[PDB]
Image 1 (cartoon, rainbow over the protein chains, first blue to last red):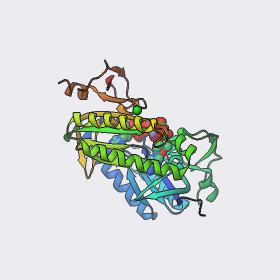
Image 2 (cartoon, rainbow over the protein chains, first blue to last red):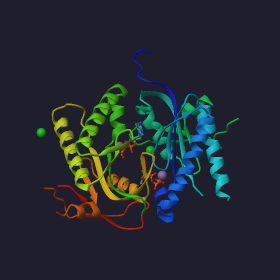
Image 3 (spheres, chains in turn brown, blue):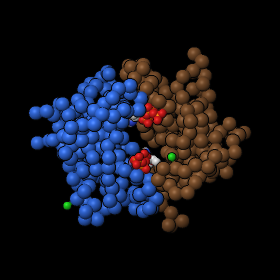
Image 4 (cartoon, each protein chain N blue to C red):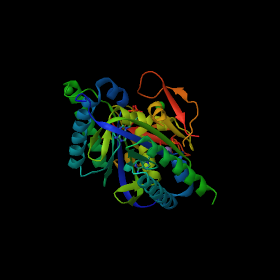
Length: 163
Length: 166
Ligand SMILES: C[C@H]1O[C@@H](n2cnc3c(N)ncnc32)C[C@@H]1OP(=O)(O)OP(=O)(O)OP(=O)(O)O
Ligand SMILES: C[C@H]1O[C@@H](n2cnc3c(N)ncnc32)C[C@@H]1OP(=O)(O)OP(=O)(O)OP(=O)(O)O
Ligand SMILES: [Cl-]
Ligand SMILES: [Cl-]
Ligand SMILES: [Mn+2]
Ligand SMILES: [Mn+2]
């Protein structure tokens, strides 16, 4: 479609809950070790689901996938790993959305990138939220969804938690 | 706090999502590409280094607080002058500046002072440059500041006095 800027991509954001407080409690040396380990785990899981880490945001990542099932499986695997590690507790919120986005270098721009970020911002620590398009596109179980408004967007959006 | 002393500046466009929605992706990408070019130019003029882009804003490192503050002043000026001439859609940008030790890892920066700089920027109004007390105090010797405001910052136990550039 000529009027369409940008190509379809699934965008996933992760974000550690209360990372600043954690950093203050454990100190910078321990924080650097922690985020280094976390980066490696996330990187490895993304690679397993054929995604690409676009960038780090300090205590989380922006990630691109071709298919929604890849992004959701990556999220499920990360949450499972964070739970496993805590029984030796970093909590992460994950949001997933899909739509056209504009590529510039390795980065992605446009309203669907913003949407993915707000879906993630809506998620509780330990939760994976996905937008309706992702839910509709998808051995994965979802809740019945919840209506929310997102910062910068008009109207309401139904977001679905992975169960 | 660990690592080498550095000044950290964050920029962030106010309500960029609403703007993107209003003008559409074609216009947004043109705007953000032009904004990136402007910021990159001003950063280079003050010997700074852009660490990363965060969509509608940048994380920038400087050796000296005067460089970071001069950069913020030049940016706010350019943005106001550009908006006044309809050079691009009006954008208002928040700017926060903090200094202290942070850990280098690759080309990124980590630690509580990075988080502090991000929170200082988050407190700034669109069109404002807010700096932490160490930055204000470091410039005590043609840059003027207000009398500061005391604020709580998420994730920090303290109360912190933040100063706007006048
Ligand atoms: C205070 C903000 O600092 C961000 N931050 C830390 N290091 C970096 C970095 N190297 N690059 C970019 N950003 C960085 C992450 C942190 O933002 P939040 O995730 O909003 O803070 P926090 O995790 O404390 O609170 P919540 O996520 O629970 O809201
Ligand atoms: C909704 C979130 O999407 C962020 N965003 C958009 N594109 C990118 C990108 N390529 N890389 C990283 N982040 C991106 C910016 C936006 O976050 P905010 O700046 O908090 O949104 P907004 O400008 O609407 O809110 P305020 O700055 O007014 O709080
Ligand atoms: Cl939101
Ligand atoms: Cl003017
Ligand atoms: Mn966080
Ligand atoms: Mn913004």
